[PDB]
Amino acid sequence: MNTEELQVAAFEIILNSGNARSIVHEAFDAMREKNYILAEQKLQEANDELLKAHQAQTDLLQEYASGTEIKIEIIMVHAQDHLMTTMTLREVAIEMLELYKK
Amino acid sequence: MNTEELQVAAFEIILNSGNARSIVHEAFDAMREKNYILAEQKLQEANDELLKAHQAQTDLLQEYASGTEIKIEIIMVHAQDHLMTTMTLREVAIEMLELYKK
Amino acid sequence: MNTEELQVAAFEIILNSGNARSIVHEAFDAMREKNYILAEQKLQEANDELLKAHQAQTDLLQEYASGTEIKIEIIMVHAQDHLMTTMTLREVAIEMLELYKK
């Protein structure tokens, strides 16, 4: 509350997203080595992580929608970028597994 | 410019870009069916939908360029991330549709 | 930090990441032409440019972390989105170049 709380939220998204991101990179490394089983399971481990971050964002979006004021701050922005850009990396990774497999 | 006008601009962006994004996954789904012409086309629908969000974003910063003050808000950050992340997913999808066609 | 400084910073990020994005697209065009040499090289130039953008974002974050106040403006959000989607886009591309080869 409030500035400290938002800093914690920001960091929750960033730690968890950064985790998701190298897990998505592990998955890329696997498909590189024709090992699709590893790539696929890593693709789901990154999901596990990524939604911890997603939920953090959602809870933050929920507080705003309801009226409690949230003053942005560059670390929030950077966090959000990191979630959403990691989500999109993973969306790409999935689709690329599918070409790989042929 | 007022908090309500901005909230609207946001959901607009989020709404149109969410829609463009599902459309891009439709084009992905089509590259999986080997429907390379469907996919080509959905990438165009997606583009028609995105230009909407995109236009909204560009007017907001145009409005900002011209001196109007815009307090941020987490849903705007989130709207911009949707547009820019959706746009980039689409760029990936164009490139991957080429790859598929080989 | 400091309106003039933050607008400068934001434009530095947008211009350099904009350039890195076009170079990444060069790498995609060069992939498409079967030319894996150029594409690999272009992915490194894109990186040379992106780095300038990442540095400026890092200085801002590090400034923020040291207690300096920073009112984010849409232009900054937009610049950060350009940096982080452009990074994500290089990342896919590095992978896609790999797949082009296989």
Image (tube, coloured by chain):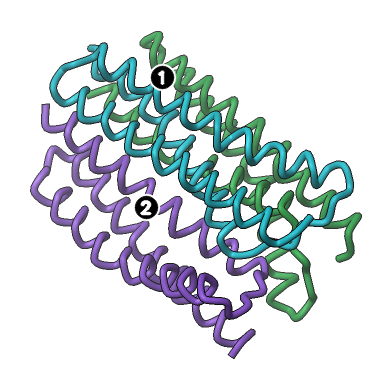
Chain colours: A purple, B cyan, C green
Residue at x 19%, y 29% (from the top left corner): A99
Circle 1: residue type? Gln
Residue A91 seen: yes
Position above or below: A84 against B92: below
Based on the displayed image, in which of its 4 quarters is residue C15 positioned?
top right
Q: Residue furthest bottom?
A: A1
Horizontally, residue C4 falls left or right of residue C79, namely: right
Residue A29 location, x and y as percent?
A: 25, 46
Instruction: Identify the image quadrant of the N terminus of chain B.
Output: bottom right
- Report the mark closest to the observer, 2 or 1: 1
Element under disc 2: helix
Circle 2: residue type? Met
* Marks 2 & 1 on one chain: no
Residue A15 seen: no
Horizontally, residue A55 falls left or right of residue B53, namely: left
Q: How far apart are the two marked residues, 2 and 1, measured between alpha carbons?
A: 23 Å
Instruction: Identify the image quadrant of the C terminus of chain B.
Output: top left
Residue A85 location, x and y as percent?
A: 45, 50
Residue A4 location, x and y as percent?
A: 60, 87
Residue on which disc 2 sits? A87
Horizontally, residue C8 falls left or right of residue C100, namely: right
Residue at x 79%, y 43% (from the top left corner): B63
Q: Which of A16 and B87 is in front in this view?
A: B87
